Structures are given as structure tokens and as C-alpha cells.
Image: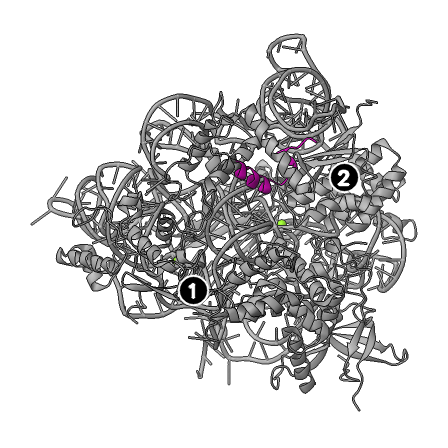
Amino acid sequence: PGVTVKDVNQQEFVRALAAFLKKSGKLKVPEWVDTVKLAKHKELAPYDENWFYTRAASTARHLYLRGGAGVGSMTKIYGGRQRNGVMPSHFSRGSKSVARRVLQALEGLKMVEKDQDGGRKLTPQGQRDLDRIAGQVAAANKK
Amino acid sequence: RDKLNNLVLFDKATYDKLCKEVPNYKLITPAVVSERLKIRGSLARAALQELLSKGLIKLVSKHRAQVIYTRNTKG
Amino acid sequence: MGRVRTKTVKKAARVIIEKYYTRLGNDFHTNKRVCEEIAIIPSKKLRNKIAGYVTHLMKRIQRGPVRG
Amino acid sequence: DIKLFGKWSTDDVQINDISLQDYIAVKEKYAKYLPHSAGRYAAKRFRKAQCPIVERLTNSMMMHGRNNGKKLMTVRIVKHAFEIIHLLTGENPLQVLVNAIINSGPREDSTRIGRAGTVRRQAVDVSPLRRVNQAIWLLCTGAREAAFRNIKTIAECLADELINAAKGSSNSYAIKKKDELERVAKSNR
Amino acid sequence: RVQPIKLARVTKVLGRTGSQGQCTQVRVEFMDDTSRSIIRNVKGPVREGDVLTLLESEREARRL
Amino acid sequence: VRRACYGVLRFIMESGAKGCEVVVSGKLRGQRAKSMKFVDGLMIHSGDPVNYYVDTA
Amino acid sequence: SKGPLQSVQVFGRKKTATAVAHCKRGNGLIKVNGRPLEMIEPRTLQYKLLEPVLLLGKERFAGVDIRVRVKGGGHVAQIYAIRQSISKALVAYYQKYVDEASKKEIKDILIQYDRTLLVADPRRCESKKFGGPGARARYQKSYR
Amino acid sequence: MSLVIPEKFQHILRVLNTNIDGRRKIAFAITAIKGVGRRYAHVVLRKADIDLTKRAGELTEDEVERVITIMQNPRQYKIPDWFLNRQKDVKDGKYSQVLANGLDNKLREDLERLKKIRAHRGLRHFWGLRVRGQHTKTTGRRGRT
RNA sequence: CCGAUAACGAACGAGACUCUGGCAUGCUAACUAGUUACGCGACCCCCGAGCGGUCGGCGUCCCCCAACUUCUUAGAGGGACAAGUGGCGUUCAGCCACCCGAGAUUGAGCAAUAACAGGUCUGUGAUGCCCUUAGAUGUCCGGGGCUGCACGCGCGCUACACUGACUGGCUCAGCGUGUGCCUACCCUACGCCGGCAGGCGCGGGUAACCCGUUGAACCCCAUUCGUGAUGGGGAUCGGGGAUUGCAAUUAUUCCCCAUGAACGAGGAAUUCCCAGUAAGUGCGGGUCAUAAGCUUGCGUUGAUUAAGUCCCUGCCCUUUGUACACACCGCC
Ligand SMILES: [Mg+2]
Ligand SMILES: [Mg+2]
């Protein structure tokens, strides 16, 4: 019955773990979450109020796939498409502060720890929790 | 062909029509029901999943760009 | 189409056959090894083209009186 | 057996006239699971005939800037359209598509460089390959014209176009242009 | 009174026509009567052996 | 100029080569510029081998 | 019991995307990049990945474990590299571990449906020249 | 629930000095007011604690004035100072935000300030030319012919 | 090219040639590239699986303390030649189809004689002649402008939408570059502050070692909008904050909040293109203190049509007429 997050859909997994963080009220949510945009290239605010939980889930899943990635790596991953107005579109990264605060809050629940080199990785506690959540979403997908 | 001024919220004169004939034909899609009932289309999408919740209309697709429903099996 | 040879490969092929007829047959892969020691051919793309026209001529020389 | 999109086998379809059996590729030999194959069919003349007609329609359904490489969106569009025509008719989508092709192919056209009377001066019958090509192109253009500015989606526009062409209604854009071309060719025989 | 739509099968390909190559001229034979055969011109790519429809009985035949 | 070019070409061919070509351009004789080419022997112009076959000055 | 040294690593390349299929003796299992074959990004083109196992049945895959790594190309090129890797690794496995009579009667099934499963596509790209914005398209010129 | 339209549903709403459309969603209906932008709407509604999924006309009468005063007094509801328009005011230095014909007459106030000081930008505005230094060689001909 | 042949013997160009792409489980090799296996772990799974699954987590050139080169890199070589079969052909040169093959036409560079009053004396300490040379056309500095706008044209970028926009998730590339003789000026990891452009402190990298497994865009999946010049469009313009420099006003650029204008697929005409091609989406480089709506090499997604023609526009060869030879934009 071994369940791994890589063995199921990641897009459903991020919803499943965002639900976990929503019901588990331990996230250190800053006061400006209702105002800022997730990226410089993004014109409009997010629609879902639990977007901070969604970002935390997504970066936890990314750190499962590979560790050692810093805030610059996070914003490089979360970059998108800037339409540049009338100029031809280009690629731009997301807000550094949002990813920095998400990562900082991920130390609060003690599942992400900084590394001996640059960046941060998952604790064994986090490695337990990710697949623990993956088990139930796999069960739901099967049934 | 100037404007369509569709319905964003149901009046009773549309909802009574919705109750009886919408779950009575095969190809029921948001665009088709919007053009038949002169409704906005976002309202059509909302009412379509409400009829799904009522359970007398089956889904087939559930796609981000093309959601498709159908009536129940008869005969 | 577009596979017509030039006198550069045609002149060499005629000469080597009538100098070394006893050492040639109707196998291109055999002849392309034959042409290696009997002629210092600067190009790989040329030695096989030289050998290919030889086999075309070797088929005809075993049948009738070719001009060579 | 092939179960294109997991269903709609090609075993039960037929072509009513032998004039198109040589080119339409709904046979079991030309049966494919999924209409996406980089077959290099443009590398030689008459190689698109053995190409499956579904793949041909998928390739031809993208036009006008917005859609020139969005093959995945085109495949999902064709999948939804076939599911929709199956819902609306109750029979195999492939037979509906083949019948639409046959009833959409214009049996004649007209063309001249000399001083034409109205449009073209001499009428000439088309090849069956041109028949199939013009049928697919007319279907794609008709769906796009129907869906240029309206709430209906590409899959449903393709669905109604295929159904109208398969039954014969003089309302589909493809059969309308077919009748117009035949009438002009008849006038300028 | 109306002539029915019929089918004819290509025997051999002659060449292009129309001062641009926009139409190819080929000889065809009736599947209804094998001995019956004419020569026509067709637009679009045609190889030998395929069968093509014919709404009209006889239109044109010229020696280039 | 014409005597000197002939002497130079004679010297080059006497030194031993498959061919040589000399081009002199400028205000020869009158005001109108005219170019004189003295070419002899084998002389290729195209392809890779020209780089290590000809010497250009 | 624990008979070792029955494994191959066969590559498959398509449009700069190369995929190596680590075929290993064991239970019937298929995975790419540590992910299951169905649990994969292109839900639209999942049928192309399912195509080899569809045409050959899980019975031929019973003693087959496949681990595929891809480190190049795009998305659909990645798909085609993966499926070609699966097919090529399987035919190599049947070639060098069992009779090539079986290898031939499994080769012909692939070749009679899709020859791209055994032969890579020679086309990669074409160089863009300095005359226009594309490889062959030229900048729009005007005379007046 | 896709319920019927409420009896007390207003197809248009009079706010400030203009009108909006109740037939559309609230977060884009309130953007019809001059000076009220899309992001400004999407932040003031979140800070004014309403539901986005509802339309405009079924906002209650007290909710309308609550949104009105929330937008009109942004400083005292934790709206960031950098989200406004007349920040670091040219006249009185206050970090204020104006969302009405007050914005229009304030813009005209700044325009006549530039004209009175006869600065380069003021002269360009008065003549109707460009002010940001963009080229006038081949553009801006619609305003003349 | 074969053939004839008052020609013979030749040469240039084309070709031949060089670079790249396409097969090489053949060889040489690889801790500045990896792959398998083993041993530790870390987690899931434990009912019990236990060679169960994942790990871009740690080690096995930490010198005896694993092998191997398929995947990666680049050298040596091979391989393709109409080679084979059938058909057409003076059975000659050659052409078509097909098997087997990775490939049966990959793209470029190079590119003859002769000429243009084609462009550059604003590339040169290439240069004749003429001009100036102290109130200078030398040379430096301050400032302005080269952007200036009733108007016309050319190359482009964004658009007119629903095959869409926006929001969130998922997720894959290759060219080529990075700290300085003068010459000052690099590419950036990580951590903290801020929403942002940015700021601060610590590193790595003169480089397959660090940026960088280049976590790119498009595309894919879910949410909302719903045919409304509308959540398409972002032009003009107000205000605020940073960065570059001695200097940003005539806005260098970038960020944010403000208004949302014309534009609903555009005449007469006209450009380019046959497969990885067009087209969409890009990435680098160039100019760069700051800079890309330009250009250049490379990637990604990826077509419809066609294997013909002289109809228009031109070109090649022969014959032909000429009152043209500044050569029909001729002459008269
Ligand atoms: Mg709005
Ligand atoms: Mg050459």
C-alpha cells in the first residue's frame, strides 16, 4: 500500500494538501495577503482567499521533488508571462517577498529546514506528512 | 442583431420553463441553454451544475473549456 | 532525378577498369575496397561514386563491347 | 477493436460509393487510437490519402494566427465534437463524419484564365483527392465562420456542421458553397 | 429526362492543360461499359486507376 | 606597369607553379580608372581548397 | 530466485528529446521519472503512451520492469521519446534474452501499426538565415 | 443556488455622481465609476467584507453605503498608502485617493497649475501635443486630420 | 553527361570541396559528464509484503575504497553509391516505382569572364586634387538638437476576441555568454527588509566545476468572465517609488494606483513560403553606465495546399528581323 506523491496527480495533490493546511490553523499569514499580487507580471489579484495555503502546498510538493532551492529558485519556478502592454511579451519572475514569507512560515510548522549549503529542504517530518496526505488522495482517486 | 440583453438572474417566467423542458433533450450545454432561454451563460453554467446536484441531468465531459451534459436514459 | 555523373568520375572509372579488369567484379562493396589501393582518392564521397559507376560499366562490359 | 478515444470502432463504418474508398482512411489498416501522428505525410505526393481522415481534419482545423500549433487543443476539440455528435444522433461518429465528407465534396468546379463570363469560363470536374480536401477545408472554415463571434464553442459548431452536412440541409456552409460551386459550373459548362 | 450521375475510371495520364498546369488531362473509361471510353480534363492531383464522378456525359476532347 | 607585370609573371611561372594571376587597378593612363588582369596557368576560384591552394596578396 | 544481470538500458530520441528505458527483469511495472504511466502530464496524448502496452498486452510485460528518464526536448517530443524508448527496450529485451523468433513476431506488430516506434525521426530543425525572420520566410520587401 | 432575481434588485445603482450596472458582477460593476480601477475594487471589496460571487443589484442599501465609505476613507482601513492615486499631494501633501468628478477637477487643477507656471509639460498640454517626449513625426495625426 | 561532330587538345564556373543534421548498444575514453549495482540512510507502506516504492539524499579518485560508456561529451573510423529488383529509354547517357536501409533530394559557406560612372574620401596613420589652418572646417569644454509635427510612404510590435481573457496548479528545451592592457564597467546562488523596481551581508565562477538538472514561454489541467468596443485592447494622460550616471526636463528604464481612446478582421494593390516548412511561442548575442517594438544563430508547438506551368512577372539556349549599340527608359 505504499503511496508516493509522485504516484498520483500533483494538481489534485496540491488541492488536497491546501485543504490540510486550511483545516490545520498553524500558518503564519501576514497582514497584507488581501492586497498584493503573487507576481510582478500578474495584472489581477487571486480569486481564491486560500491562495497562501495553495502556494504553501505547491512549494511543499516542489521541495518533495527536489530540495535545496532558495527563494530565487522559487520565484524562477513561479514566473510566468508578462504581456508588456503593447511591447512583445516576455518572461518574468514572481514576487520574492511572497515566496520568502511562505518559506519562512514553513519553518513554523517544522517541516522545512535550511540546509548546510544554500537553500532549504524538507525535514523527515515533512517527508512523512507529504506521503501521509498522498495516501488519502490516492484512496479517494481510486474510490 | 444589435444586442442580446440576456438574463443574468432567472425570473419565474424562465425558471418554470427551466424546470420542465431543460432536462428533456440530449445536447444540453451552457451555450445551447443560454441561446434557448435568453440567459447570460454564466447563469446557465451555474444552473447546469444546480441541475447536476438535483441529479436528473448526467455529465459526460467536465472540461475547463467544454462542459457537456445530457438527459437520463429513457426507453 | 539529378543523378547524372560528371566526366571527373566518368574518366577515372573507365581508366581503372581497363587497367585492372582482372581485379573487378559486379559487387560495389568489393570494388570500393579495390579502388582504395589502386588510386589515392581524396574524398570518401568520391571513391564510392567512382566504384558505383564501375559496377554500372562492369555489368555492361560482361555483356557486350563497351567503348572501353 | 482500435477504439479511437477508447470507443467508436472503425469496423462498423462504410463508404457508400467506391469513388472515395481509395482515399478515406477509416479502414482497420488505417485505424488509429489517437488522431496525433507525425507521419511525415507531406514528404511525397498522394501520401496524405493513406493518412487517417481524422488526423487530416485535426491538422486542418487550426487556422488564422490564433491556432497554428495548438494540436492538443484541436484534438480535445475534435474529441468533444465527436462525443457531442454521438450524443445528438445515437450512432457512430465516424460514419457521420464520412457521410458529411461525401455529401460535402463538390463533384465539379470551374476555372479559366481566359476572359470568363461571370467568375470562371470553363467548368472542370475535380479529382476525388480534391473532393476530400475541399470537403475538410469547407467544414473547418464553416465551423470557424459560425464561431467567429458567438457564444457557441468550436466543438459544438463542428458538431452541427457535421450533422447538417451528413444529412443534407442546405444550411451548412460547406454544402451551401458546394451547391453554389456546382451551380456556377453548371452555368459555365 | 435528366442525365444520371455516373462514374468513370482513369486508364492513363496524358498531361497538364490550362496554360498553367492547373488542370490535368486524362483518359477515362466507363465502369458501366468497359469498351466505352473518353478523355477529359480534371483539376487537382490524379494518379492512374482511381475512379472519379461525372455529372455530365461528354464535354471536351482536344489534341494538343 | 605592363613591362613590370610581365616580368613578375615570368618570374612566378619560372619559380614553378600551376598558375598565377595579377590584377592592377587605378588611375592608369587617363583620368578614367582601368583595371588590367594578367592571368595564366590553372586558376581555381571556388570551394574550400582555394584557401590552401592560392596565395592572396 | 534472485537471478541477476537481466536488464537493458535502451534509449529513444525524438526532436532533441532523448529517453532511456531501463528495462529490468521483475514484476510487470512501468514508470517514467518516478511517475506512473497513467499519472502523467499529457492527459490528451495519454493514448500514445498506452499504445505499446495496448498492442502487446500486459502478458508480454509480466516479467518486465521499465524505468524511463528524460532530460531534454519539449512535451510531445518527450512523449514520443518515451514511447519509442519503451518499444525499443522491449524488442531489445526479447532479442537478447529470448528467441528472436519471438522478437520478430513482436517487432512486426509495432512496425505494422507505427514505424516511429522503431525508427527515430531524422528531422530536427533548420538553420535560420539572415534574410528574414525564419529559416525560409523572408522579410517583406516593398518597391515604393 | 441559482435562485430567482430578488424583488428588491436594482438593475442600476446610483453611487457618488455616476451610475453602475446591476446586471454584472459587483467587482467589475463598481469599476464604472471614474477613478475606481479593477485592482482598487478587488481590494476594497475584500476589506469591506462582501461576497464576490454575488451581483451588484442585490447588495443591500446599508452595504452600498458601507462600500462607499470604505472606498472614500481608505487610510483608516489598512489600505496600503501606495495603492492610492493622489499620493504625496502636489498641493497639500496628503496621501489621499479621489474617485469621482473630484478626480476630474483635481486633474484640471494640476493642468492649470502647469499652465500657470508655463512649464514645458503645461505648454505641451495646452497646445495639445505629446508631453512625455514620444515622437510626433508619424503619429497623432488623428487629432488633426 | 551520352552521342554525333572541322575539329583536336585543354582550362574556369557548376560539380568536385569544407561545416552542420540524420545511424552508428563498434573502438578510444572520461570526479569539470554520467549510467547501473551495492552499502547507509530519509519517508511512505506495513495486515505481511522487504530485490515493495521514491529520493537531483549520502558514499563507493576521501587513491584502492564497484563496474560500465548505452544515455552525455569528441576523435578516429565506417555508412549511401542509383547499390539491388521491376518498368521506360538509341538499352547509351539517363528517368519512375519499390524492397532492404537512419538517411534513396538536410541545410549552408565557397562561388567563373566581364561590367555598373551602383554605395562608401562619415573605418583607417588607404589616398590624389581642391579647401581651411589661430577670430580654424584642428582640438577641448558649457548648452541645444539630431526625437523637433497641418501631411505621405516603408519595416515592424500589439490588437479586434470565447480555438479567448484572467486566476491557481501541473510541467518540459537548445544556441551562446559571464569580472576587463589601455578601460573605470561581470554572470549571479543563498539569507534578511520591502508589495514592487530595488537595498544589505555573505558566497561560487576566468568556467561541461558557479549561476545552471539553465524548473522559459506557448501548450496542459481546474475557476471566473459570457458576445456587451465587455474581465478583448492598453493608446494618451495624472500622481507616487526605485535603479543608471556628473547630469533623466523634451518624461533613459522599471514598479504601483489611476482614464480606457481608435480598433468588430481593414479598397485600389501588395509580400513571403513546399517540412520541421510557414505560422504561434521563445532563448541568447549585437549595440548596452541604463536599455530592445530592430537584427542575428539556436529551441519549443506545429499545419492546409502542390511534385505543374508559361497566364502575368523574369531568366537560359537556338533560329529570326532590326534603321538600336548612351543598346526599347533605344531610335524616330
Ligand atoms: Mg470591472
Ligand atoms: Mg562550386
Q: Is residue E52 magenta?
A: no
Residue range highlighted in magenta: A1-20
Crowdedness near tag 2: few (<14), some (14–19) or many (≥20) residues, C-alpha within 10 Å: many
* Amino acid of disc 1: Arg
Is any part of residue C20 visible from this angle?
A: no
Q: Chain of mark 2?
A: G
Q: Position of residue A64 (x, y in %)?
A: 57, 31
Disc 1 on helix, strand or loop? loop
Magenta stretch: dominant SS? Answer: helix
Identify residue for label 1: H23
A10 part of magenta stretch? yes
Question: Could you tell me residue D159's position as x and y percent?
Answer: 66, 66
* Residue type at tag 2: Lys
Residue at image location 76% in from the left, 84% down from the top: E59
| Disc 2 secondary structure class | helix
Q: Specify the quadrant of the image occupied by residue I7.
A: bottom right
The chain containing the residue under callout 1 comes to: H
Here the colouring is one colour
Q: Position of residue A32 (x, y in %)?
A: 37, 40
Would residue G89 be found to the left or right of residue I198 on screen?
Answer: right
